[PDB]
Length: 129
Image 1: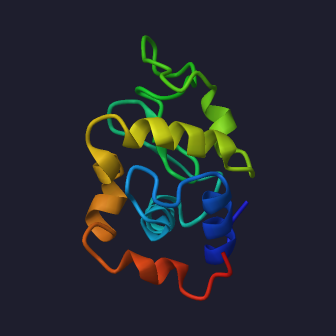
Image 2 (image 1 turned 120 degrees about the vertical axis):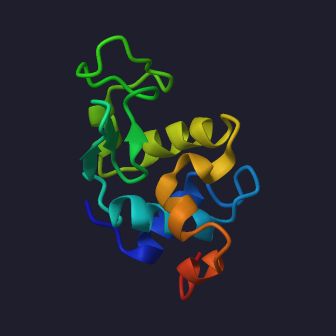
């Protein structure tokens, strides 16, 4: 699934990302835009042999099992395929663990590079939430 901006904002808000750990909803929508272009099936390989999965580009090195990163952790206790689902619940629940893991949203390099410090409230412009 490729979400619309406000469609994704609504789904994220329903699943509790709005202000989660003090990060307003626009942060999360912005992170998704630049991590995945709102595409639930986005995957990008990392140079170390892990892969980033789904709408929030979660890393299989630590967070999910894809069988392809032998000896890696599965801290969300889910297969990585689940993070490519058209429904975002698994990705959100895992993202909540990631954002609480000591670095806030700095975990997402695209958020750091393109959202951090900007007017992230712009990302929910015109949304009916």
